[PDB]
Image (cartoon, coloured by chain):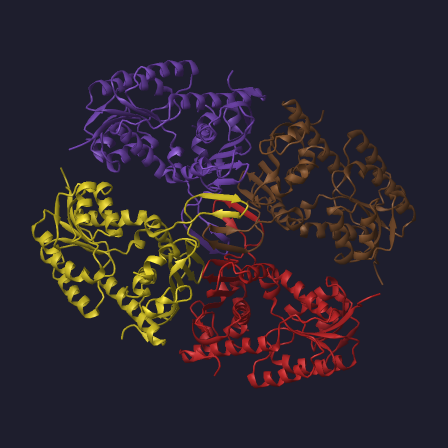
Chain colours: A brown, B yellow, C red, D purple
Amino acid sequence: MTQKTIKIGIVGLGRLGKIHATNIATKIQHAKLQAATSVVPAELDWAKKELGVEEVFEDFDDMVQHADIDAVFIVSPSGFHLQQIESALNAGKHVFSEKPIGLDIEAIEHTQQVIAQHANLKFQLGFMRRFDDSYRYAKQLVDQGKIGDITLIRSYSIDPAAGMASFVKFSGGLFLDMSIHDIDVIRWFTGKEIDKVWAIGLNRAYPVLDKAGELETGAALMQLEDKTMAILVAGRNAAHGYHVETEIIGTKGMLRIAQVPEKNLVTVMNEEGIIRPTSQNFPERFAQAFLSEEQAFVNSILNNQDVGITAEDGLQGTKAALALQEAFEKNDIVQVAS
Amino acid sequence: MTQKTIKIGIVGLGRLGKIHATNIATKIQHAKLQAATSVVPAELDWAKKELGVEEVFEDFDDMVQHADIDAVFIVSPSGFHLQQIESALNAGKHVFSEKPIGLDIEAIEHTQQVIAQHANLKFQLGFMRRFDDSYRYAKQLVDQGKIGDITLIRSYSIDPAAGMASFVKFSGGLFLDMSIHDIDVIRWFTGKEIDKVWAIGLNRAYPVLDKAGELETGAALMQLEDKTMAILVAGRNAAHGYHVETEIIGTKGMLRIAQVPEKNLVTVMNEEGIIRPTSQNFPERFAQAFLSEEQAFVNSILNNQDVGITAEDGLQGTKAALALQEAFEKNDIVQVAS
Amino acid sequence: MTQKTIKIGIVGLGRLGKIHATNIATKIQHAKLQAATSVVPAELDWAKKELGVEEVFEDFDDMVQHADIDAVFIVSPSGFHLQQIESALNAGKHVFSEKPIGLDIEAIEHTQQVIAQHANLKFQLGFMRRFDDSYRYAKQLVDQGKIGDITLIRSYSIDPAAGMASFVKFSGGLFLDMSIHDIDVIRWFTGKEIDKVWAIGLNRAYPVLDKAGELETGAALMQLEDKTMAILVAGRNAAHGYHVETEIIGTKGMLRIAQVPEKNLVTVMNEEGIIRPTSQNFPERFAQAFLSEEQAFVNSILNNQDVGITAEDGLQGTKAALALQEAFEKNDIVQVAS
Amino acid sequence: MTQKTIKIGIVGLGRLGKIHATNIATKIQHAKLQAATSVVPAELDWAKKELGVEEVFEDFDDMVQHADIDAVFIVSPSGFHLQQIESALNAGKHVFSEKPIGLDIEAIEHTQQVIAQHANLKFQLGFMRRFDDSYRYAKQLVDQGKIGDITLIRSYSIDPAAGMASFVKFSGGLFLDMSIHDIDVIRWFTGKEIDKVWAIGLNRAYPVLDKAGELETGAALMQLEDKTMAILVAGRNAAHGYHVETEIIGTKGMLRIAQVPEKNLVTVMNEEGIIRPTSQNFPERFAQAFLSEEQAFVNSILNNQDVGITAEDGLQGTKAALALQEAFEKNDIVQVAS
C-alpha cells in the first residue's frame, strides 16, 4: 500500500508538547507517535499510559540515534532548539520545531548552515497562525488584491489575566515570548522586512515585574523597509480572555482578524446587556491551526513538498524580537539589521 | 415675520405626556406649550413651575373652548381619545393623538366621519416608529427595491422586566398595549392588510397574570392579503432591556432593525466577555423619533402639508390588535375583517 | 491491543453520503470504511479509487449479509431508511441512520419494534445539531438554569438561493425537508412535546413551486404541551448564505445561536460598509458536528454506551413535520397527536 | 422673565461654521444668531436669507465693536483664532473658539494672559468629543473605576477616501489637522501629560503628498508622564467611511468607543454577507456632540458656570501635535516639553 506511516518522536511534554503529542497520536493521518524524550519521569509515564508510546528516553540524542522514528517534534524550552535541530538532522530525521528557532543570532546562523547541508530533509517552524482558517482567509483577500497595498498592520497578542499569578513567580522578555508570531504575521502578509523599531512598556498592575526585568504590557511602533507601518501590543493581563487580533489597513480597504475573540456562535442577553463569550487561552483559540500545521508537516514528508516556512523566517523573527527588547531597555529607536 | 408660533395645549401628563410637553416647550421650533389639562393637581403645578405653561384646566372641553391654542396633543388614557379628538376638531383645533385612536370599532368610525368633516385641520396619530432614523433608513432600502418584494416580517416588542412588578398590580390586553406599533410597521412597509391571525401566550414567570386576563409573553402568526407572512412577539419581561426589533425578509435580501438594542457605540470587554450595553426603556430608544414626529406635526400646520398618517391607519391598527386578542382567547384562527 | 477497529459499510453516496464516507475513512478514530452500496456505478468507483473501499455492492441486503462489517451508515433516500434499518439490525449490525427515520407513522412503529428486539445493538439518528459546539454550549447554559424556564423558541432553517434553480426542477415538502432538525432542537432543549401547530407559506420568488406542491418559504407557530411557544421559519431562498439560527427566550434571559451565520473571525471594511462573510452551505456550517456525531457513534459501540438519540426522537420529528404539512394544506390548526 | 436670550455673532462660514450657525439659529435654546462676519459675499447672503441674520460684517473687529451681541463663535481658519479671541474678550464678549487655539506656542501664551485678564468672561474650545454621548459613557465607566487605572489608549481618526481628491489639490500637517481631538481625549481620560513621541508616515496611495509635505496616513507611539502608553493613527484615506475609534485598556478591563463606525441600528444581509452601514463624515458622526457643546456654552453664560475646557487644554493639544510633526520630520523621538 502506498505512502505509509511517519513515525514521530517528541521532546518536550509541557502544555504545548502534550497538545502536539495527543494530536499526533490520535488525530493526525499517516502518523504514529513512536517515541518521547523527557527528563521528568511523570511525563514519560503519561506518554506510555495515555498515548501508548512504545519507546521512552531520558536523553534526546539517545532517542534520535536509537528510536524507530522518521521525524522529530521539538517542543523543548527555546534554549535547546538549535542543538536538538542539528542533532536530529545529522541523524537523518525530518524536523518540526516550535518557535523560536533559537535565541542567539550567531548560533542560529550555524544551524542555518546545518539545515542547508540537509536539503533532502524537511524543516518546519511552528508558526501556526499561517495555518489558521481566519488568517488564511485574510491572506487570500490580500493576495487577490482586495485591499490594495498594505499601509499599516496592527497586531495584538495579550495573554489572559488568569495566568498572571503564575507568571509573577515564574522568561526571556515580553516581545520574545509574546510577539514572535506577530512579527511573523507582518512578514508573511507583506513580504517585507522590519527596519527600525521603538518599544515602550509598563508594569502598572504588577510592578514586581520591574525588578524581574519583565513587562506586563508593552507597545511598539515599527517602520518597515518600504516605510510600511506596524503597531504591536503584547501583554499578559487581558481581563476578557486570550486576545489575539490582527488588523490590516490597505489602500483600498481594511480588515480585522478577531476584532474580538469570539468563542463560538452564541450570543447571550441578560441583565448585563448583550454578551459574546470569548476564547480563554491559546489551545482553545488555535486548536485547528495546531492540527493543520501538524498534518502539513506529515504530508510534506509523504509528498516531498516544502511547506515554505524556513530557518530564515525563524532568524528574522528572533532578530526583530531582540531589536524590540533592545529598544525597550534603551528607550530609543533601534535598527533591526544592527 | 413669516410663519409664526403654533400654540399647543396638552391633555395627559403621565410619563409619555411629560415627554411630549417637555419637548414642545423646550426643543420644538415654532411651537409654544400654552395650555395643559389634567385632573391631577400636582401635574398642573408641574406644568406651571417646570414648563411655565400659562393656562391650566381641569376639563378638556374647557381648555379647547377657552385657551389661546391652535392645536392639541392628546396623551390621555386610550378610552378618552375619540371624544377628545372630536371635541378638539369641532372647536377648530389641529389634533395630534397618541395611539391607539380608540378601542371600539363603531365609535372609531364615528370619529372618522368627524375627521372627514374637518379636512382643513391636521390630524396625526403618534406612530413614532415611522419617524425613527433606523426605521426610515430601512424603509428607504425597501422603497428603492433593494430587498425585492417582502415575504416575511418579524417584529418583537418586549418591555423590560424592570416594569413587571408595577404591571402585576397595575390593562386592555397585551397585543393592544404592545403590538399596535408592530401592526402599523407591517402595514407601513408592505402597503398590505392583515387577513387572518392566530395568537398564543403564556404567563410562565408571573402566573398571577392568568387570573387578571393579562399576558406576560405572546406570539402571533399572521397571513396578509397577498399571502405575506408576519410574526409578532410581545412581552413584558425582557431581562436585557427594551427589545424592539423588526426583521424584513425579501426575495433579494433581508434586513434587521435593532437585531439587538444597542445603547451607544461603546463595547466593554471584561471577565464576563464582550459586552454591548443596551437601551433600557422606550423614552431612551425613541427619543429622536418623538422629537421628529412632534416637529413634523408643527411643520404640517405651518406648511399646510399632510403627514400621511390617517385615522384609517388608526382603525386598522386597533382592528388587528382586537383580532389578535380574540384569537388568543378562542385559541383559534380569526379573520381580521370580521 | 484493546478496543479494536469498527468496520463500517455505507449506503447512499450522494452529497451527504460522501461527507460521512470521507470522514469515516480519513478522520474518525477506530473506524474503517470497509464496504459501500450504491446502484450508481460511478459512485462505487469513486469509493474504491478515492477512499480505497474494499467491498462494493449493488444491493443493500447483499452488503449486510456478506461484507466484513460491524456497523452500517444509512444515507439513502428517506423512503429506504426503515427497510434498511430493519435489515441491518436483523443481520446483527449496529446502525447509524440519517434523518428522517421514515415517512409513514405505521411503518415507523413497526421499526421501533424491531429496534426494541435488538437492544444489544446501537441505533443512532443523524440529528447532528446535538453535537454542534455552539448548540451544546447553549444547552449547557440552559441545563445550568442560566436563562430559567424556556418560554419561547424561534428556529430558522433557510437554504441558500444558490440552490433554488436546481430545486425548481428537482421532494416530500418544505417542513419535512428543512424543519426536522428544528423540531428536534425544540424537543431537545425543552424536554416537552408539540401539541398544536399552524403553518403558512408562500411562493413569491418562484411561483412555479405552487403547481409542484412545494414551498419556497414557510412559517409556523406551535404551542407545546405546557403552553410553551415555538416559531419556525423554513426556506430555500436566503440571499446571504445558509441561515440556521435558534433563539431561546427564558424567564431570566435570552440567547441566540448564530444570530447571523458568521463564516470565521474576519471582518472586512470597504466602500460597502462593515462586512462579515457568511457560511454558505450545510457542509461548511456543520463540518464539526458531522465529525463529532460520527465519532460518538463509533465510541458508543466500543464503550457500549447509549448516545441518547432514539427511534422515538425520530418518530416525533416525523410526526410534527407531517402535522406542519397538514396544517399548511388545510390552512388550519392541527393537533400533532392526531 | 428670567435668564434671557444670548445674542451670538459668528465668524467663519465654511462647512463647520455653517453647522454651528444653523444649530444656533434653529435648535439651541436661549440663543439667537444675531451677526455674521465673512469676507466672502455669498456667505453673508446665505446667512441673511437662510438664517435671517440681522447684522452682517466684512471685518471681525467691526462686528465685535458694533454688533448687538453678547458672545462670539470663532470658526475662522486656525491662523486667525488667537487675534480674534483677544479682540472679542477685549470688547467684553464671551468666546467659543474652534480648535486649535492657535499654531504658535509664544502667541498662545500671550492669549492665555489676555484670557486670564478677563476671568468674568466664558472661554470655551471646541473639543466636541467631550460632549459626545458615547465618549461620555466611557468616561463615566472610567471615573467609576470600572476598568481600573489606564495602561494604554489607542485612538484613530481617519477621514473618508471621498475627500482625498479635494485634499490633494487643497494644510498645516496631518497630526495638527487630524489628531488634536485624539490628543485631547488622551489628556481628558487620563489626567496626565504626554512626555515623548515618535511618529512615522507614508504616502502610498497618493505619493504626490510627499512633495507637498503632507501625509495620507501616519502613526505615532507616545509615552505619557507616568509611563502610560498611547497609540495614534491619523489618515485621510478610509475606504469604509469616517473612522474615529478610541480604545482604552485598563488594569481591570478594556473598552472601545466605535470599534466600527456604525451608522444606525440597521443590519443588511444579502449576497455580500452581513453588512453594517457606516457613518460617512464628521457632521453625521458628531451631530449630537456639536449641539451639546453649543448648548453647554450658552448655558455656561446664563448660569455663570465654567465648562472646564481651558486655554491650557488648547495649548497642550497644539504642543503635542507640533511634537508629533517634529518627530515625523526628524524621524526620531521628540520630547514634548521642548
Q: Position of residue B203 (x, y in %)?
A: 39, 67
Q: Residue at x 70, y 34 (%)?
A: A176
Query: Which sits in the foreground, B63 or C16?
Result: B63
Q: Quadrant of the C terminus of chain B?
A: bottom left
Q: Position of residue D233 (x, y in %)?
A: 52, 32
Q: Residue at x 47, y 83 (%)?
A: C338
Q: Position of residue B103 (x, y in %)?
A: 23, 66
Question: How many numbered marks does the figure carry?
Answer: 0
Residue positioned most to the right: A66
Residue positioned most to the left: B66
Residue B98 makes an appearance in the image: yes
Q: Is residue B296 left or right of residue A15?
A: left
Residue A146 makes an appearance in the image: no
Q: Residue at x 59, y 83 (%)?
A: C108
Q: Is residue B121 left or right of residue B251?
A: left
Q: Quadrant of the N terminus of chain B?
A: top left
Q: Is residue D64 above or below residue C37?
A: above
Query: Which sits in the foreground, C322 or B170?
Result: B170
Q: Is residue D28 left or right of residue D225?
A: left
Query: Which sits in the foreground, C229 or C171?
Result: C229
Q: Position of residue C53 (x, y in %)?
A: 77, 70
Q: Is residue D185 above or below residue C173?
A: above
Residue C31 falls in which quadrant of the image?
Answer: bottom right
